[PDB]
Length: 217
Ligand SMILES: O=c1c2sc(Cl)cc2n2c(=S)[nH]nc2n1CC1CC1
Figure: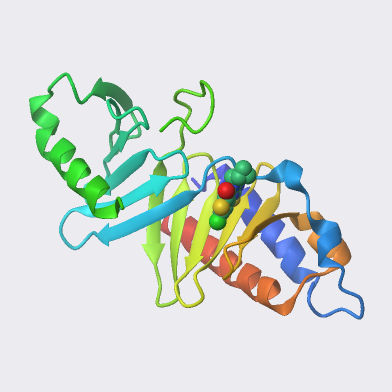
């Protein structure tokens, strides 16, 4: 095996859910907000063509990746040129679009079409590489579940277009609501101060989704 970050996340979710944080005489959800736990990376767009090629995604920094159906991964860094390719074993190989690798043209070509299908820059100084990639994903009737290589799990809920970003290193959750406002909470402080029924319900769903990620392994 079980991934250690997913195991930690499962325990954190078990603890907050066991406190029944919405079933309280006094709910003070704002006191659990902690902007120091803000996620640096989240998935801003995705496109599911896994029936034929794979799942495309774009991160907040405008890098794009495709997780292909062979469990290999090709990422185009936000500079438009630098490529990271991850094998099924996890071995990482760094290339450029300028240099031409024949064994990867088809995947490189697909990545460009996926990028443009999702499309309608350095978002900060330096910060090259150490970019997370999509480890695995699955979808249900109500959500898509995205597990990133930095241990974060993002759950996008189709119906109301809300999102949860769970970070096990900081034991935090960021909730993006239908208005698209984002707020970051420490899970332990949600236990202490309570939260609304909606967030409590999504955290129960999240734990069920993390169980799935761990059972699939
Ligand atoms: O603009 C965003 C948005 S918009 C939605 Cl939705 C989620 C996020 N987000 C997370 S999550 N972490 N950081 C961000 N930022 C960056 C701004 C603080 C500088």
